[PDB]
Image: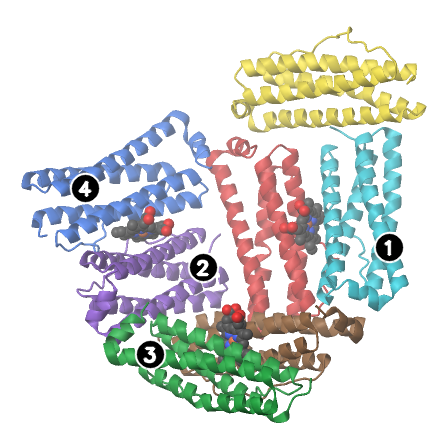
Chain colours: A green, B brown, C cyan, D red, E yellow, F purple, G blue
Amino acid sequence: MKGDKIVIQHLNKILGNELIAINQYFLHARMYEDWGLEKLGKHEYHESIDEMKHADKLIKRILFLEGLPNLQELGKLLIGEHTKEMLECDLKLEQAGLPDLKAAIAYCESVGDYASRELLEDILESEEDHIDWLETQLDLIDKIGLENYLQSQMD
Amino acid sequence: MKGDKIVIQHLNKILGNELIAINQYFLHARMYEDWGLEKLGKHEYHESIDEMKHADKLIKRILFLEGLPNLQELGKLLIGEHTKEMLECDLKLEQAGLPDLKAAIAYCESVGDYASRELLEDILESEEDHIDWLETQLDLIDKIGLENYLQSQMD
Amino acid sequence: MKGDKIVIQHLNKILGNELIAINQYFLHARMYEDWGLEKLGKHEYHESIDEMKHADKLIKRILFLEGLPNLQELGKLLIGEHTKEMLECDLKLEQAGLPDLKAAIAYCESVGDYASRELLEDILESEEDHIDWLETQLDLIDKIGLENYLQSQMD
Amino acid sequence: MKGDKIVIQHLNKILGNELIAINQYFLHARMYEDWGLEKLGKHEYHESIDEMKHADKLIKRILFLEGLPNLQELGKLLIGEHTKEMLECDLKLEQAGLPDLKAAIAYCESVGDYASRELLEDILESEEDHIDWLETQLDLIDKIGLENYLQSQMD
Amino acid sequence: MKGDKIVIQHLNKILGNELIAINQYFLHARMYEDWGLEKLGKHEYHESIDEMKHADKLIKRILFLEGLPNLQELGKLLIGEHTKEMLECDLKLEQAGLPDLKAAIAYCESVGDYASRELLEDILESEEDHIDWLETQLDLIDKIGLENYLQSQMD
Amino acid sequence: MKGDKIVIQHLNKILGNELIAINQYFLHARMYEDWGLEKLGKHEYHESIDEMKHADKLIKRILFLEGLPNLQELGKLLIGEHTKEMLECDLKLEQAGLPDLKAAIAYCESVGDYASRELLEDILESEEDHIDWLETQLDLIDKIGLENYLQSQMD
Amino acid sequence: MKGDKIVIQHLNKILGNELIAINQYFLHARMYEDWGLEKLGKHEYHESIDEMKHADKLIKRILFLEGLPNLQELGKLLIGEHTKEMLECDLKLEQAGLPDLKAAIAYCESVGDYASRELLEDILESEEDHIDWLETQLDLIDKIGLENYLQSQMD
Ligand code: HEM
Ligand code: HEM
Ligand code: HEM
């Protein structure tokens, strides 16, 4: 089925954001498990896999709309060097991708592409859940301290 | 454990090649399923997952050697538009990726990094298996014809 | 027990024929799997294993008759290069092996070695089944075409 | 995939050695069971099956490298007449194949055919285990005597 | 069904041989058990039971052909007094019973009594198996010694 | 099978290092469990068991090569007094045996003792994993503090 | 809990004896399995493991008494060249072990370290059982001969 060109452009932009998130989250997850923080590494790995599933869904939607997925464009990775830094980098990545999803949802509503809007709404809910988790982790770091928090992530 | 810098550079080169393969294979797999070729799409998806696991193993090895994985650089993907074309593109990608693995194995032998050598040997064996599969598919296309071959890829 | 010398000579001749068949069928089976023809490869592998069991049975019979099995002699191998050629080579070998079995059965009747005749009768019944299968495959090739036939051997 | 011609030659030579071992070990196994020595016959049969699997692996590797396996050439078998001679013949045959395997592994190292090196290394370890077993049996014959040794091989 | 009179005579002769075998083998088995050689006694008992089944089959075949089974004639038993002697006696009986079976099979072929020929062929195969076992046991005695051999027959 | 004398010398040196590691790790595990740090005690116990298996494998290889294992010589023991000190002592011991394994692997490659090279390669991989765990533990001590770290080792 | 210094000295001496026994028994077990003597190898392996558990118990007891286990010093190792000689060496080691255990038990009685006496009593009973087994094996060698004895150790 032929889709709207601007809808395909929005889907490609979201796909590029998801591609950035996949690499950033996987590298963060692997650097967490390297330091012995199995809990944080496992959670970041699960979030990365969720990002891969989001990218797969976007690729399927673009292909159904007779568009061309853009896997080539990989943007800047926001990689941190310590646990707090990587948590803030992940939160900033999540926040920076939120306006794009909202704009895509609004445009899909405006031109009557309701299935794409439903898919983007599911993606937006997932991104909001990740944002909530990251903010909760940072607040916990503030409440209990860095050492206690890092101890809680040991196992 | 501190590793050799040149070994880190070789591992980063292989990791970049693996990322290229991941993106190209996932795109080809999802374009196969869109055409109704479930079998070819499933095999391409499995190949992409294997490339993902190779990239994960390389990232783990680089992080163990106190290096910095380079996931930021994504090179040119060889994306095809018809089944024969994308099979040939995958074959070209695999053939181009072989010399880097062999050079990395030779260097690991030279400097005595034997665990990295075993890792790269496993990766090389997997790449050779994929090459064998791709060549078998192309020869089967030449033997039984494109129309017969594409029919067997349904379901 | 001590058997007839000429019976042992006939058994040795059939054993050499079976060894030739083992080698040819195993090579054909392996080059079938390499091309991607799983069905033909599996059937040729099973036929090869049947030839191996026949050779083992002949070795046991020769040993019981206080003779020396002759595994040193390996004659000409009729190795084909394309599927039809392989099938015709196997059929030609199987047809050339038949007169020796019939002559040996007749001789075992002449001198009253009835257990050896029963063994050779079982072997001959198996060889006739292999001939029937090969002829059926060639007739199917001539009936449905080479490309259609090769597609059915993919899986 | 096209491999090195000299690597294919080494693989073919090792395949011929494996075929010789297959024939010799099967004949020895069968003449062991004829004497009532079930244990020695069973172990020789298992060794012959292992040699068959080695030959199969070599055939597959040669086929992958786009070469022609040489099943035609079968060299001299080292057949014994009593148990001690059979064991010494098997040990001599196994020790005469180690230099070929070692040279092939060294050459595969030289030209960077690492998958072939891994295959040859696996079969070399198997041959070394067979040599260990043969030497242990020959030393046990001298430790406990021929009559005591043959009695333990009955059941 | 009315059979051929000479076929009935041959069957009666074979039955008379089978009865002698039954008695001799049962007696040998019982003295083997009495001496404490449970393994040899068990094998001899099984051999006697097999001869018993052969006699039963012969009686059934004679009765089907409207003939009169002759169980009255019991000829001389070859009873031994030590293990080697009774193994040799069994071998002598089994070898002396062979020409009658072969002559009966030849006559059944000549007159066209094919079912009787199949029965006698099965009997002949069994007798050959017993001959093989007896010769193997005697060769084992000559190879490992009487004292070692008898120790293996305790259980 | 007779092996190279220098290869046996290298294996003997590695075996002595393994025995040193066995004794030191067992003592460290016992004092860890004595202080009430069950997790550290359990991991040190498992590491000591792994060292025991390494020593067993080396002894088997030396005996197969017709050499004489040197269990008599046991070198100095790097015994620590506190958790940080014993972790550092274990890391130093593991780093001080790595060059020996690397030199042994290089020599086994040079003279063609490939099975010994594979055994030493497996041992080297195990020692590298132990080094990774020890460095991770020390970095975790630095990250979360000694008091927090020791609390997590209680259960 | 603080214990007597002399009790700790006795425990350390017993621990050194146990370490000597561990090394000697493991080496003897390995060469027993190398020669093909599975029964003797398995029993020596189990005896060695029992010695390891004895040493572990002694280490725990020394650590509980707030002492310092002496794992460093490894004394003479009575290694034999043939089965009879190694059995005599093991018996000599076990017999030389006894007086130290008896003196330690008597001293623990004298100063009222009753738990240590119970531990040493269990160890003494185990050593007495090993002595009984070793003397039984030597008496069996005398009764049935070396060649007959070694045959029973094959499997
Ligand atoms: C640096 C890049 C990537 C790495 C290191 C990576 C790694 C992985 C790993 C280790 C798995 C686990 C496989 C398993 O457990 O069987 C996985 C699963 C998966 N990945 Fe990736 N991946 C990457 C990029 C991508 C991309 C770009 C996509 C899609 C556009 C993708 C799609 C998937 C899917 C669909 C799965 C399976 C999900 C499931 O089984 O439920 N991945 N990946
Ligand atoms: C004198 C020559 C040979 C004899 C008498 C012989 C005999 C046998 C027998 C009796 C079996 C057992 C099959 C079963 O139990 O199902 C067997 C298995 C096998 N043979 Fe041989 N064989 C010979 C040569 C070869 C050769 C030349 C090859 C390959 C080049 C080969 C490859 C195999 C394989 C792959 C198996 C199956 C192993 C398995 O299923 O685990 N054999 N052979
Ligand atoms: C010096 C050379 C040594 C060698 C070659 C050796 C070898 C072994 C082996 C092969 C095992 C079997 C592990 C398993 O089956 O999972 C084992 C277990 C064990 N070893 Fe070591 N060991 C040595 C020294 C020691 C020492 C010095 C001690 C104590 C002071 C010790 C204590 C133990 C214990 C407690 C076990 C567990 C046994 C069980 O769980 O049943 N070992 N050893």
Answer left or right for E19 relative to C104. Answer: left
Whole-angstrom CA distance, mark 1 to mark 3, is 72 Å
Q: Establish whether ligand 3 lies closer than 8 Å to the Cβ of label 2.
A: no
Give the residue type at disc 1. Answer: Thr
Residue labelled 1 has its Cβ within 8 Å of some atom of ligand 2 = no
The alpha-carbon separation of the residues under discs 3 and 4 comes to: 55 Å
Q: Looking at the image, which residue sits at the far top?
A: E72
Tell me the amino acid under the disc marked 3: Thr
Look at mark 1 in the image and give the residue it sits on: C136
Q: Quadrant of residue C1?
A: top right
Q: Which residue is mark 3?
A: A136
Q: Residue at point 59% right, 29% down?
A: E143
Badge 1: how crowded within 10 Å, few (<14), some, or many (20+)?
Answer: few
Q: Whole-Å distance between the Cαs marked 1 and 2?
A: 59 Å
**Residue ID at (67%, 18%):** E48
Find the distance from the CA under tag 4 to the CA under tag 2.
Answer: 46 Å
Residue D105, image x, y percentages: 56, 66
Assess whether mark 3 and mark 2 are in contact (beta carbons under 8 angstroms).
no
Task: For mark 1, name the chain.
Answer: C
Above or below, comparing residue E42 to residue A67 in the picture: above
Check the residue under mark 4 and report the chain it is in: G
Tell me, yes or no, if residue F21 can be seen here: no
* Front-lying residue, F130 or B143: B143
Using the numbered discs, state the Cα–Cα distance from disc 1 to disc 4 in whole angstroms.
Answer: 81 Å
Of badges 3 and 4, the one in the foreground is 3
Disc marking residue F4: 2
